[PDB]
Amino acid sequence: TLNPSARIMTFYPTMEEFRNFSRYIAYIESQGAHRAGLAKVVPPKEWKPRASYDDIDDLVIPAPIQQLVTGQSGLFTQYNIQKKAMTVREFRKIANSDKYCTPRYSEFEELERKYWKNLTFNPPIYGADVNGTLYEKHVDEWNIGRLRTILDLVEKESGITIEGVNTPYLYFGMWKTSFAWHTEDMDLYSINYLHFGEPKSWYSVPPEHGKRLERLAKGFFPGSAQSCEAFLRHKMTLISPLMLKKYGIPFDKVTQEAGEFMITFPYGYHAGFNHGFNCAESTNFATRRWIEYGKQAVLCSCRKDMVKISMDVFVRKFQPERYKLWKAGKDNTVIDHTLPTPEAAEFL
Amino acid sequence: ARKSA
Ligand SMILES: O=C(O)CNC(=O)C(=O)O
Ligand code: NI
Ligand SMILES: [Zn+2]
């Protein structure tokens, strides 16, 4: 019906559509965008999150990670080793230097090839997980610091703050820096804006096929699966498109350019890599449709202090008629990944 | 608790 091919969709809102975030997410879901697990949203040309990016050179990256990768035949494991702090200024110099810079290429496929050929050599440094926002306090549209979604009920009612989830994160990339296959904490949505710099390429598995990817990864890494059910949440596992194709996992790819938003959808598996020096800002968010995902999310057991959000406030507020049953462990609801969020009543 | 890469 709506995106029967489940391919990644791109959207081009007017400033008027840009004004209401939750509504536009509802709209693109009514168009089937969520079926791919990932979507691109290009803001109108007039919109800018900030006027200029040169006043940021003194911003500190407290905990850079060197990404060491081991593996073969399209299956890899990534070990992130923490490094001493540096500024953006210092990071740019290392990123744009001849050792870590993007190699020469004609078309994207070549660069993609070089990424999967070279990802275990010359480990790069990733400026990840930096608390902060590059938005300007007066930008009211699609502000990653305040999106006004129902996820706020974690802070506003329960008083809990979870860094990177209900607060913004910055990511300073260089060539070959990557993010492994994962869904979001509590299978939330995420939003990602590339502020400036070289592109970020993404891979995505449709939520309706997510279980097939999990079985695949379990088969490849049984030791890891025995130790933790949700081990993919460790964000250590890299699997090439050739392997996905070989084993019959549906997926799509898309490249994100400076000034573009990417939205990931509940239980969308995604992975990717940065083309060169860049800066991205990201956070999680939610809609009504997410509540059932949150209730059913399989979480990491093996590590201390992992992100676990109490679903109680959500069930209580948006599903009062199911609350008693849910508290009793008797809620048998099955998720249909193809369905849009209820907020799209008007659009359909 | 925080988000980790
Ligand atoms: O930008 C990165 O390195 C990783 N980002 C995400 O996984 C996301 O935005 O959901
Ligand atoms: Ni993600
Ligand atoms: Zn675990």
Image: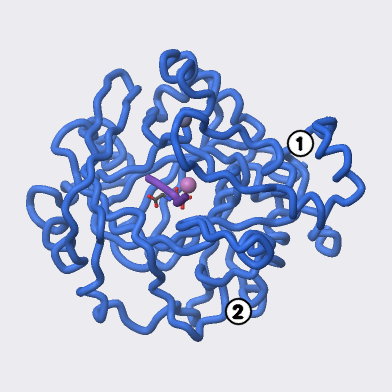
Chain colours: A blue, B purple
Residue A15, numbered circle: 2
Q: Is residue A301 above or below residue A290?
A: above
- Residue located 46% across and 25% down the image: A244
Q: Which residue is mark 1?
A: A335
Residue A42, numbered circle: none
Check the residue under mark 1 and report the chain it is in.
A
Mark earlier in primary sequence (2, 1): 2
Does dot 1 land on a helix, a strand or a loop? loop
Give residue A36's quadrant in the image.
Answer: top right
Report x, y in % for residue A30. 75, 55
- Work out how far the residue at label 2 is from the one at label 1, CA to CA, in angstroms: 33 Å
- Residue located 79% across and 49% down the image: A315
- Residue located 21% across and 66% down the image: A88
Closer to viewer: mark 2 or mark 1 = 1
Residue neighbourhood size for the residue with mark 1, other residues' Cα within 10 Å, grouped as few (<14), some (14–19), many (≥20)? few
- Asked if residue A259 can be seen in this view, the reply is yes
